[PDB]
Image: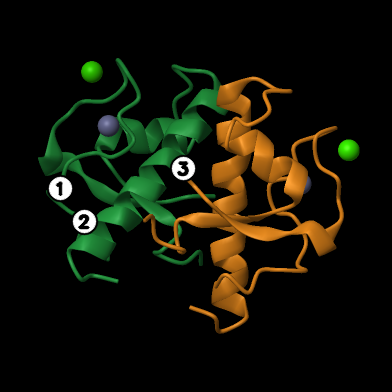
Chain colours: A orange, B green
Amino acid sequence: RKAARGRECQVRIPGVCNGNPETSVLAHIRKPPDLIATIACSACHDEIDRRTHFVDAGYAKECALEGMARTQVIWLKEGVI
Amino acid sequence: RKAARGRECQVRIPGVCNGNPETSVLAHIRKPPDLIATIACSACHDEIDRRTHFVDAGYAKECALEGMARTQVIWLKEGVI
Ligand SMILES: [Ca+2]
Ligand SMILES: [Ca+2]
Ligand SMILES: [Zn+2]
Ligand SMILES: [Zn+2]
């Protein structure tokens, strides 16, 4: 599942997102399981982890978890899970 | 997984939650898959689905998805998934 590298960001915080799938990683939602994670570009990853705080933490969290649900939905369709 | 019946609500919107696990069901997050769902008491279920709108929709969504992550984490621990 850590092979979400090079996929589209599912977090997509406006402004913060870089939209560049080359930067995408499996970003764990806060040894946590890879299921409980979202594909996130480098920028969104730093924001959802609160290494940056460009946006409100509730909104970041909302986007992170929305991203997690989209990611799991991708895994479902693709046969990954 | 629809055997989340009688478990504790993982959504727990303050005020809205009834806290009564007898009312709990597997509430799908919006034929969607049961993975993309949370254990929710009857009250939280109606709120996250927007049948009631006691709280802000962004906050409800946040709680719903947080509930989904907690539920999946329960499924992981319990061997359900
Ligand atoms: Ca940007
Ligand atoms: Ca109550
Ligand atoms: Zn992004
Ligand atoms: Zn509840």
Per the image, the residue denoted by label 2 is B4
Residues indicated by labels 1 and 2 sit on the same polypeptide chain? yes
The chain identifier of the residue carrying mark 2 reads B
Subunit of mark 1?
Answer: B
Label 3 is found on which chain of the structure?
B
> For the C terminus of chain B, which image quadrant?
bottom left
For the residues bearing labels 1 and 2, Cβ distance under 8 angstroms? yes
Q: CA distance from mark 1 to mark 2?
A: 6 Å
Task: Classify mark 3: helix, strand or loop.
Answer: helix
SS at badge 1? loop
Q: What SS does tag 2 mark?
A: loop
Number of marks drawn: 3
Query: Assess mark 1: CB under 8 A from ligand 4?
Result: no
B34 and A73: which is toward the camera: A73
Residue type beneath disc 1? Arg
Are there few (<14), some (14-19), or many (20+) residues within 10 Å of tag 2? some
Sequence order check, earlier mark of 3 and 1: 1
Q: Which residue is mark 3?
A: B65
Task: Give the image location of residue A69, x and y in percent.
Answer: 55, 55
| Disc ID at residue B7 | 1
Residue type at mark 2 is: Ala
Q: Quick check: can you spot residue B47?
A: yes
| Marks 3 and 1 share the same chain | yes
Q: Is residue A22 above or below residue A45?
A: below
